[PDB]
Length: 125
Image 1 (cartoon, one colour):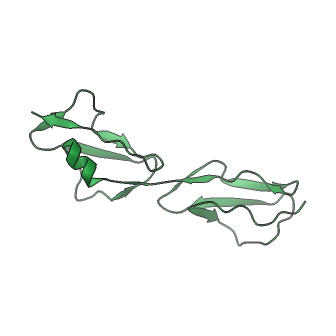
Image 2: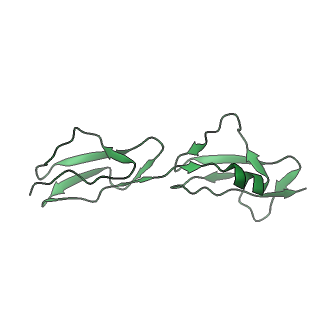
Image 3: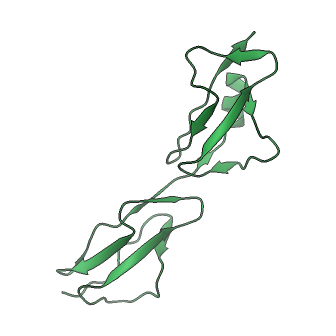
């Protein structure tokens, strides 16, 4: 019932010293790299010669100056804001000077989720 190494996952790995073979009833813990967010079971187990299903690392979002330019918006915090936001982080925007929030836009704060971030839209006053 021994297992080989636990499955590799993209953008993350186990937190322990690696073994080449694992006894049944072993477990391991995964961590995702900094900018990524674990989804699934952080700890998996070797039973019946197999590993239970490893988790996934959800992607950060890269803020787009071009979409902001097209939608007539700007960051609320231009000096502070990192280019990469994590899954689950929100970004706050403002309309550019002399523009106002469109009626069918979202409002000025959106949330990053596994590489996708929506943006609000403003229209000229």
